[PDB]
Image (tube, coloured by chain):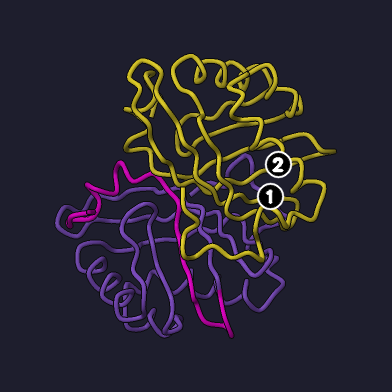
Chain colours: A yellow, B purple
Amino acid sequence: IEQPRWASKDSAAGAASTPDEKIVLEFMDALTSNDAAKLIEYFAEDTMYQNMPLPPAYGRDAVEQTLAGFFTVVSVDAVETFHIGSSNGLVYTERVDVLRALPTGKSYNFSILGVFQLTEGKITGWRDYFDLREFEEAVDLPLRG
Amino acid sequence: IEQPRWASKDSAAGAASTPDEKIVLEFMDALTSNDAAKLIEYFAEDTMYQNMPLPPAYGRDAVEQTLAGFFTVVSVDAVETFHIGSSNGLVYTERVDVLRALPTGKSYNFSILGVFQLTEGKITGWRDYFDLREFEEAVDLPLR
């Protein structure tokens, strides 16, 4: 993965300068664990996770069930974060996620802009925006959308 | 268009508090014009516009021709911005755009998170991240 031409080092991952920004970057790194039990500990009880516009998961239990199910069929092979920033209680990651489908071996680069809302350092909302055209094929599950 | 359960008034569009954030909202309200020539006045000469991951447009001419083409087959009927924010010289909009295809009259709700880079009050970069599964059918053009 090459740094796009629009990347700005003023907003680079290395330049994260708030506790919320730094926790999110740590959480980006943990995604390659493909461990739902490890990822869930970043989340408040009152939380939500959604890849738009698929049905949202609300509450810790639903978020963990969703992640564990995703890790059953896909491996997050790499997370490259070009931009991270924050504003008005929200954190934004502009990034690429490399996903590999386990039954097929095929790999997929997804360009993702994600928003995170943290409360006392725990994730209260997580929403990723990206194209789903190849997400259906990448993910051997009905996505209900 | 309903306000989502996750909407935070702390970052609502009515609370925009920088010049760059205020311009980006104005550009949001101007989208319903469907007028590439009124919209291009917002862009600097070195600029780019991309609906991720489609082939980007670099340079103000290419951005103009991309919008002009889009507005030939699609109307932007509404833009609701739930959140506007900014950080490290980038502005972010979490919003919904209602798009209507001209040849069919079918409408579509696109949930969109966009990032804007502005230099001297002019757009040097604009990337919208959203699901393009229905965008193929929405715009009567090859997506490449």
Residue at point 66%, 30% (across, down): A30
The foreground one among A133 and B112 is A133
Mark 2 vs mark 1: same chain?
yes
- Quadrant in the picture for the C terminus of chain B: bottom left
Q: SS at mark 1?
A: strand
As measured in the structure, the alpha-carbon distance from the residue carrying label 2 to the one carrying label 1 is: 8 Å
Q: Position of residue A101 (x, y in %)?
A: 39, 23
- Which type of secondary structure does the marked residue at label 2 adopt? helix
Q: In the displayed structure, would residue B60 be above or below residue A136?
A: below
Label 2 Cα crowd, 10 Å radius (few <14 / some 14-19 / many 20+): many
Q: Label 1: which residue?
A: A91
Chain label for disc 2:
A
Per the rendering, the mark at residue B59 is: none
First along the sequence among labels 2 and 1: 2
Is the C-beta separation of discs 2 and 1 under 8 Å?
A: yes
Which residue is depicted at the point 53% across and 35% down?
A78
Amino acid found under the numbered disc labelled 2: Val
Q: Quadrant of residue B51?
A: bottom left
Given the image, on which type of amino acid does mark 1 rest? Val
For the image shown, how many numbered marks are present on the structure? Answer: 2
The segment highlighted magenta reads B118-144
Place residue A16 in its image quadrant. Answer: bottom right
Residue A88 on image: x %, y %: 74, 56
Return the mark for residue A24. 2
- B120 is higher (above) or lower (below) than B97: below
Give how far across and how far down residue A91 sits, in percent: 68, 50
Q: Is residue B127 magenta?
A: yes
What residue is rendered at 36% in x and 80% in y?
B60
Q: Is residue B43 magenta?
A: no
Q: Residue furthest front?
A: A2
Pick the residue in front: B119 or B37: B119
Report in which chain the residue with disc 1 lies: A
